[PDB]
Amino acid sequence: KVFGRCELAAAMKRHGLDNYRGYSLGNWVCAAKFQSNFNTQATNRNTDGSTDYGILQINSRWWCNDGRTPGSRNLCNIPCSALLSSDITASVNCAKKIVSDGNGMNAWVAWRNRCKGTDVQAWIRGCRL
Ligand SMILES: CC(=O)N[C@@H]1[C@@H](O)[C@H](O[C@@H]2O[C@H](CO)[C@@H](O[C@@H]3O[C@H](CO)[C@@H](O[C@@H]4O[C@H](CO)[C@@H](O[C@@H]5O[C@H](CO)[C@@H](O)[C@H](O)[C@H]5NC(C)=O)[C@H](O)[C@H]4NC(C)=O)[C@H](O)[C@H]3NC(C)=O)[C@H](O)[C@H]2NC(C)=O)[C@@H](CO)O[C@H]1O
């Protein structure tokens, strides 16, 4: 699934991400854009052999199990493939845990480099929310 911008904002809002740990909805939409281009099937390989999965590019190094990242964790207790579903419930539920893990949204490398300190409310411009 490739989500639309407001489509994803609405899904993220329904699922409770708006102001979750003080991160307004625009932060989440900005992160998803630069990490996956809003594509639930997105995957990427890290230098260490881990793989990032889904709309929020959740790293198998820490958060999900793919059977091929020796030494890794599965802190969201899900198969990484579940993070590729058209239903974002798994990804959002897992994201809530990631953002609460100490570094806030700095966990998303694209958020820190491209979203942090910028006018993120612009990512939900026009949405019926
Ligand atoms: C090629 C490429 O660029 N790929 C990227 C990919 O890297 C991106 O995925 C992200 O990867 C990074 C690096 O692997 C992940 O960042 C990890 O995440 C760890 C888990 O949250 C994090 O560990 C946590 O660190 C906290 C802060 O230090 C710990 O809490 C603190 O512990 C202190 C001392 O130990 C203690 O004194 C404090 O009380 C406490 N501080 C606070 C504020 O609470 C916490 O314990 C620890 N958690 C665990 C479970 O061990 C690492 O710090 C962090 N590494 C970094 C920043 O280098 C990140 O999670 C991945 N993101 C996602 C969404 O999966 C990917 C997505 O951005 O993009 C690809 O393109």
Image: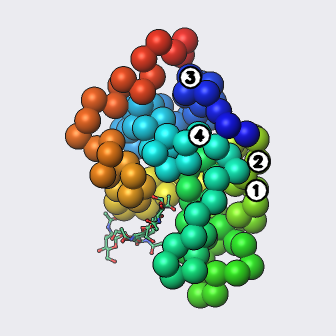
Q: Earlier in the sequence, mark 2 or mark 3?
A: 3
Residue found 72% across the figure and 73% down from its top: 66
Examine the rendered structure and indicate whether residue 59 appears above or below residue 54. Answer: below
| Camera-nearest label, 1 or 4 | 4
How was the colour assigned to the protein in this rendering?
A: rainbow
Secondary structure at badge 2 equals: loop
> Dots 1 and 2: beta carbons under 8 Å?
yes
Which quarter of the figure has residue 21?
top left
Give the amino acid at mark 3: Cys
Tag 1's secondary structure?
helix
**Numbered mark located on residue 9 in the image:** none
Local SS, label 4: loop
Looking at the rendered structure, which numbered label has been put on residue 6?
Answer: 3
Distance in Å between CA atoms under marks 4 and 2: 12 Å
In the figure, 121 relative to 51: above or below? above
Q: How many marks?
A: 4
First in residue order: circle 1 vs circle 3 = 3
Q: Nearer the viewer, mark 4 or mark 3?
A: 4
Question: Are dots 4 and 2 in contact, CB under 8 Å?
Answer: no
